[PDB]
Amino acid sequence: GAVFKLMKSDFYEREDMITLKDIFGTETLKRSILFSFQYELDFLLRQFHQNVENITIVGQKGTIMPIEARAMDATLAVILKKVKLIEITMPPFASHHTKLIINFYDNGECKIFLPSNNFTSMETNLPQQVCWCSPLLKIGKEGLPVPFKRSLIEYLNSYHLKDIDELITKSVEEVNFAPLSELEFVYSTPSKFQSSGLLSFYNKLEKLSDTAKHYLCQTSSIGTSLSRARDENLWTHLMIPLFTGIMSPPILPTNSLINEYSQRKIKPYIIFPTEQEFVTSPLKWSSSGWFHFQYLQKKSYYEMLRNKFKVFYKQDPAMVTRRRGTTPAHSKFYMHCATNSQVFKELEWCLYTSANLSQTAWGTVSRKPRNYEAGVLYHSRRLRKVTCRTFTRDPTHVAVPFTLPVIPYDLAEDECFCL
Image (tube, rainbow, N blue to C red; front, side, top):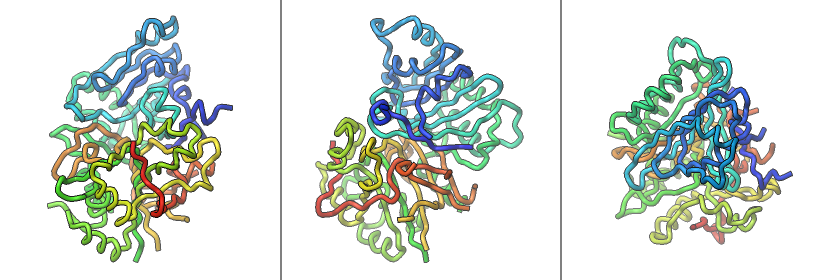
């Protein structure tokens, strides 16, 4: 079945887990179709076996690093000749952020993965990363297409590229997705013809269907305010209100929202590294470059989230391993827990995705996403509770890199890291 695994690091595991070599190094691997935001070609291609017949790479123009002659060799030369590139051009400040792997092996076997790291050595080894691995799939006629398969095809179709249609989608269509009948494929696309992002995700949660309402988000980037006039955060002012029913599509004042939260027992969480957590990371600030929250030019926005909603949470210093310490994770998780220490062991639903907490990744009720994003959704009424555990203590449906429980920011000294 599907399983979450923690990405091994050359630094943390110097002397269960997974590596890109485990994924691409198998002699039985026949073809790999890749999606990512950044490609370090010599690093990536060194992960494969000489037996591979084709490597189709989908990426944004300018994010694919060629291999210099001085760094080439006989082995790599062979791999390189099997690479086919499909470049996507995007408006400035828009991103093909999706990380996805579709492997085809000997016999009619196929497997799908969602790594949180882009394909570069630095990203793979510095921040903590995870990888969702689908159950083993096989080529063969299909009856009714599983929702996961149906959604994946819509996503691929939304690129509106002939190369994608013929070299990728046709191959995916031949695969039987029965083993994935319980999960959902959630995505974002800038396509004006395909609905996606928040709007689509909201509708899905509605269709899928006294207690404290826990809504937690773990992200590597935190977008700025949804408006230039007021301080409005995507999680606290739009997503949570929508999910709870406080609002419905055809933004309330901060204070009105705060009261609603109290009366409804809604508890918001955003896991993001503190300035001090890098001091207690094995590689110190080495992984800090991938965590972006620029609030210095609009301090009020930050103070609101930190003091008014008390939304920020950090790692439990007593539960993290010594080899990884308080090193932040570059994975993105969105989850909901209903109660009435143990919080989050059982979930109503959980989304693992490449999408950061920003308007560009999710869009809004009226605006569409600007990025390509992809993730997998686990929902209780589709499996009767989604089980989840923390890798920091290493069988559940979901496994997370952050500690469980997470600890609230000490309002007397904790501050979000600002690159």
